[PDB]
Length: 117
Length: 117
Ligand SMILES: [Cu+2]
Ligand SMILES: [Cu+2]
Image (cartoon, rainbow over all chains, first blue to last red; front, side):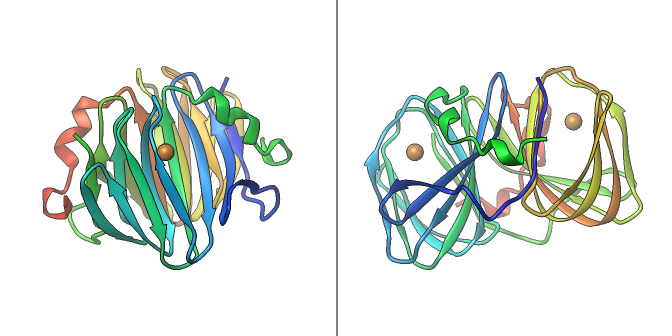
């Protein structure tokens, strides 16, 4: 059931305007995605029944979680509990790695199978 | 409760020779760490009752999972189910972000409270 995946510049897939996604790996309890986000894009306010914990690999965003707002730079991190409202403004081209728990089955369809193993 | 944390080069805790750790954030279902590893160090075989999913921010490691072995570089990722044998050889100075599920209570104390927003 273990997985390895290798980095590739290909197959980051459209999710929302300005936001591309790739599911890297997943398991019994978690699922890992990489989000590639264009400067000036945004994530609209949403909720989902998965805890979402992330790390900014590169760039700069403003991450809104309920009534908090924080500027996020490379190496910063966050944890958003299940069903909590969140959104973001993307200030520079940015890359984030985010892990969902429980496994977010709807995101398995973004798995880049050309780079698994 | 949601959580934000800011990057700091300080307060990594010695875990093994050449291997240091810091808990970045955690939540109800997950806990996120950053592993800073020195060229030439290693992790011996271990297992634990937490799923472990990781992303290599930088460097070069050989990651062993049961009878599999893979060289892992920046942007590669892995998911290791609960109780599965794994170890690693660190070939270059390396940095990994790893998320445990469920929340790994023993690692809460490695949070750097000076970086929590
Ligand atoms: Cu979300
Ligand atoms: Cu481990």
